[PDB]
Length: 159
DNA sequence: AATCGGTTGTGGTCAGCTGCTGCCACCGGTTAACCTCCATTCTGCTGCCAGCCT
Image 1 (spheres, rainbow, N blue to C red):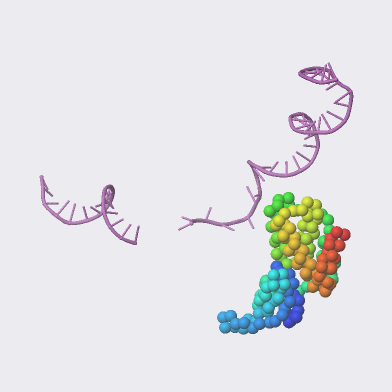
Image 2: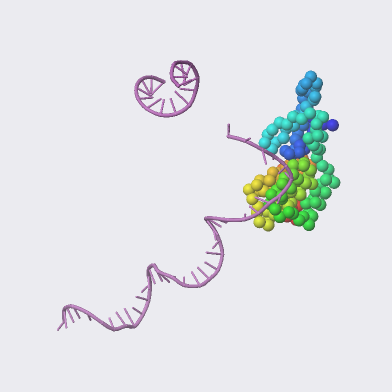
């Protein structure tokens, strides 16, 4: 499926350019690896081509995905558990899934709650992580000028 | 003429509570997928085991 030069999305790290395809040997068989150059912390990720779907690597979403995530990002009736730990584990396991809709849900919930009160060290760190990978995936989805994409996200969040 | 003590017109003044009105430290209680063991030398005492005695 994957080709050299494709821009795929890794689950917990956001965008990833597939820059080469290695052919390393483990247990005497040439399981080909693909190397991904993510840029969040400048790490090179190597995965087999077989377990790409098992680890859940995923192509970027289309314009139906864009209107779907904007539709879910502008939606009310988002009642949350009042317990701080329950809420934290809930949106952490939403963030770790790798779905654009779930990441947009986490950034809209924490954005409205930060606009309300301003939460915490851990939740501001989580909102920064989630919003930066959502901005990176959006800029990958439309080739649309990083930090101007941030202004786009701020505008569609503030509405 | 002064001279040792009062009276005080009047203008600041200066901190001493007094509310008072936030507001900010400080301390207690709560959170419910699941996962169960860290150098040498001298002196004295205390415990070890064989070895004669009834």
